[PDB]
Image (tube, rainbow, N blue to C red; front, side, top):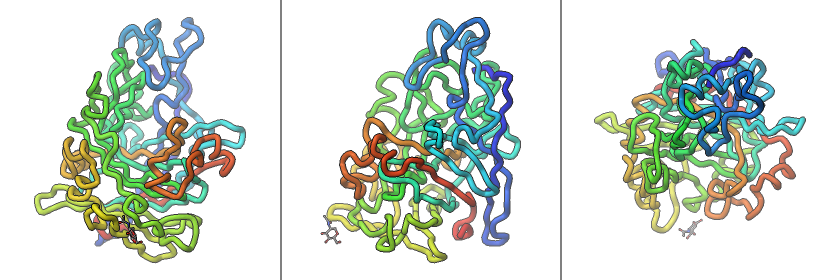
Length: 398
Ligand SMILES: *[C@@H]1O[C@H](CO)[C@@H](O)[C@H](O)[C@H]1NC(C)=O
């Protein structure tokens, strides 16, 4: 959409780059909200209205084609991110799902490089990503996410999309959702926005989930028809890793009875271990809390391969069929090697109550407990803070 007259003022965030040799050294990065989370409105004389709702093509009256859409729909800068529940303090990024005044901004943001015109492209195959988190205000049904998508580095900046990454354009993930704009261009044909994504962290105070999601395309792929569906080009389910799902129930939770105690801050390490040919083999998640390394659990379930890391053997046996079919662990790793964008978000789920994350087979949460109507009766103001985001040499971030 066309950038408007209001200026964009991105939050600055200090992150780190790590080596065994020099340790963690500070870096400047900026934060940007999703393009379609910016105010979008019609050009002067075209009246009231936006330019389409999530899940739809843009309106045919203002967006009969890409060129018209580029002129007729205006995207405004955000001069004050705190209005969207987004703030930074030094190395800390706070995402508020609900504001005191009742607004539910449910922010999703990306990491911009220091120039503010390209996303910071992380290449994590053979490397580790680490961050500190405070999950105390995330009850059942809430999802703090920190994850990677193979978005285009300039947000596919182009003639009709001049805003680019500076305005948060170019979002995609393994779900192939239809958005009214894709790569900053009117989605006239109503395609889905598909790409490989590595869900490093989808979690609340009750459960913690890690999942690669493969697509059989490189980059952002606009899918049509069945390509967007379950047997299509992306892995909607991902290869899910969650202690509760492998019959370990005392690893992560609210209280001293859990190895990771989500009433207190902790550190989340994710290692992307590559084989002798440089291909991704295994994904290893452990934690650190009160200065103690908390090692990954091992699986403990009849019919589930014995392992303490995600790999092809586990994924296959736990029925991650499209993950294997669409390129398996090696395929995830090719994406990561090409370069990925970091996204961080806080959301909830009106349709399904985030049950896949923390209910039944996946956690201690009751039926109904994660509905949005119940969340606000448990924690009125859900929020998460990620701090000291840092990546680099295996063994160097903690
Ligand atoms: C779950 O783990 C327990 C040990 O805590 C074991 O007794 C039980 O048989 C396991 N369940 C399955 C189905 O593997």
